[PDB]
Image 1 (cartoon, rainbow, N blue to C red):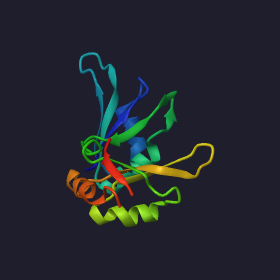
Image 2: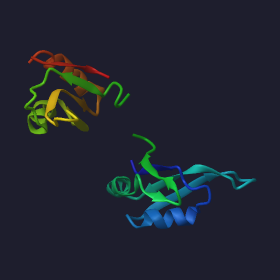
Image 3: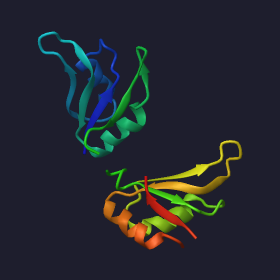
Length: 157
């Protein structure tokens, strides 16, 4: 998937100007701002389509979050449950736990699309909790049956 959506475009931005913005990353198939055809009014967003998923992937890392003309951009995917049936909440973990051990534990069940160890604000040491979202609710599911009670508890959001 190469199709991104860009949000919070300054009301006066040009499909051209937007292009220049994203062309810095890689080749684009289409780049288009949603605007009124009679009016020309911009509904504030666009669909940019890179030629490659690994560029589309970089445009996000790079452009999501930049501020041009007082508006804070947001670059994300158009076609990404998958973090709602494919989003696990883990607790009773080792307060000495790190992603390696975490990963060494979850990759066992599938692609680990994102791990998140909740740490202490003040202290920074983690806690026994964290989040791990898979890709297929299926791995997630094989994980939940497997991993509940090493101690440990897994489930969804």
